Image (cartoon, rainbow over all chains, first blue to last red):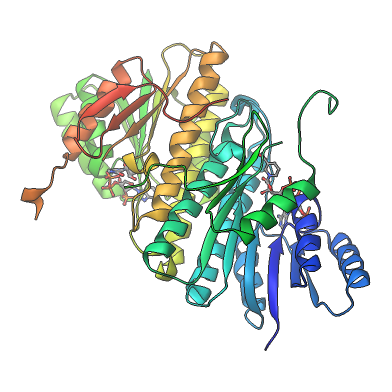
Length: 233
Length: 230
Ligand SMILES: NC(=O)c1ccc[n+]([C@@H]2O[C@H](COP(=O)([O-])OP(=O)(O)OC[C@H]3O[C@@H](n4cnc5c(N)ncnc54)[C@H](OP(=O)(O)O)[C@@H]3O)[C@@H](O)[C@H]2O)c1
Ligand SMILES: NC(=O)c1ccc[n+]([C@@H]2O[C@H](COP(=O)([O-])OP(=O)(O)OC[C@H]3O[C@@H](n4cnc5c(N)ncnc54)[C@H](OP(=O)(O)O)[C@@H]3O)[C@@H](O)[C@H]2O)c1
């Protein structure tokens, strides 16, 4: 009607959970989507305790089923979407020769199909609305192939190339909507890693700035805003 | 009895690839939706070499359960070579793209190719002489305007196949995986389907993971993996 919402898939844990909290601290109304309804309701209670005025819509749904992706987007037609974050995803690490192919089907339906459908529907309806942003969560593994993660990385090469191509297509069309891609990287005693909260801070930095790519170097773990990486014709 | 399995064999590169492997003396399993087109191709092949075994399998590979049922059928045959060539392309701006087409593209260019590849690797990785050849595109290494989603499916195919090829090498596996990346008429360079099939045979015959046509020069080059690798 008049309120604007920030939509986050995969909001029940990890980066999406902390991303919801980061946008709530910026005073944004939220629609938070995942399978674990009880975890989303917990997140909603935390957010509203911090700021009572915010609107927070819980949507429990399995986005690995194609029909649920379209029906989710239809349920959202009554809300003015300012920002869509495609963060729902998962990863399976294995040699290809003995990988669980049902998990592969899950990585494809969620990491690729759900993200591209929601991205494309959002672009269809909001391309011309000022202030809109599409933020797709890829991975550092969407720009570097990582041993024992061949199929997962391929899904993120899809996310990164799709999002870079879309961002450049929107710019060429002088569209109001912007598209951006976040590419996070990663016993804990000896190895560098970022927390989910730190990763959400990188998401916010990507949102606030006008670079298409926000990427963590897998070697140095420095986070850098940068221009598209892939070759473009 | 060993067989060369080609998906997308009813026209274009896949059709010419079947003819090229038949000239090499290979038995074939040829797969696509149009049964009558496959049956024609069989009769042309047997007109040239009557002693070859050619198996026609009409099936829609954009349906997940069909991909698995097909591979179950293929267990009755010793597969020497699997060529994942079934695919298609849709050129559009994203904002008004037919999402039905997008779904089918995802199911065919990505899902069918990765499932058949992974099943083939599971059974054949230690079998001498075996090759997996996946058909990507020069657009799987360069993003091309008005082909954003299509290119992204081909970035998947290229990165998946490069990653798998290096994984097989590291594991000292007998199986090899390779990727082919092909690229009014009178003013613009192009390759025929027949020429593209000759590039596929070159890739098959040689010791390189990538066979790619340069988008600018249209020169075909055998080369090592292109993407960054950890
Ligand atoms: N360098 C890297 O490779 C890297 C590192 C970190 C994160 N990432 C990416 O960042 C994103 C967040 O992942 P994460 O690290 O934060 O792990 P995570 O804690 O498991 O978060 C992933 C989110 O996906 C949700 N989700 C999973 N399956 C779903 C389904 N079918 N339908 C709807 N929601 C679903 C999960 O919630 P439910 O279980 O409740 O559904 C969860 O909230 C992913 O896209 C991941 O690939 C990449
Ligand atoms: N520069 C480039 O980017 C470039 C250029 C050429 C080719 N390619 C790639 O090379 C491959 C061959 O394409 P092409 O040029 O030869 O065009 P094509 O003539 O359309 O060949 C595509 C093949 O896929 C088959 N097929 C399509 N949908 C199918 C489905 N659901 N189930 C089973 N089989 C299906 C088609 O046969 P049916 O209709 O009978 O099913 C046909 O045999 C594709 O993967 C294409 O992306 C890329």
